[PDB]
Length: 117
Length: 68
Image (cartoon, rainbow over all chains, first blue to last red; front, side, top):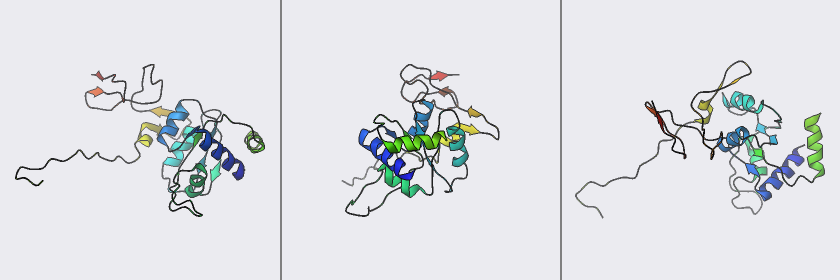
């Protein structure tokens, strides 16, 4: 669920196993070293939505939908300025391709059985 | 120091709007199409791509320039 996504993004942040952005994320997806994929839908996407769905609909690739770019951008740790409470300005990240090495969590297991269901 | 000779400028680099979405072509069917070329070297397996010039195709870092 969303707190499981928050935990796996924090684990990827502290273990540096993450590919933020879109260009190196597409590099990682065409590199075939991918485990999970996320997307914030209903944004200003005239064609990026169909590009990213035809990209993520290849093989072994999962999906998690977020309401806006501002929330997963906070979970990935993109822009952290003035961290004493609320941040100053956080820019939204579109998609995240994540490598998982420290896969020891109950949240990982419940999100994995959410993908498999 | 302002001298009577004209002053040169550093190269400003022109900003492209969503170039990666121009490489992969998405039609109405379940297929993915590659417009420009790919990379054949052992350093970059399938990741980076080549330039679409009018008389050659230039690699990003491997310098495999193939001219027609």
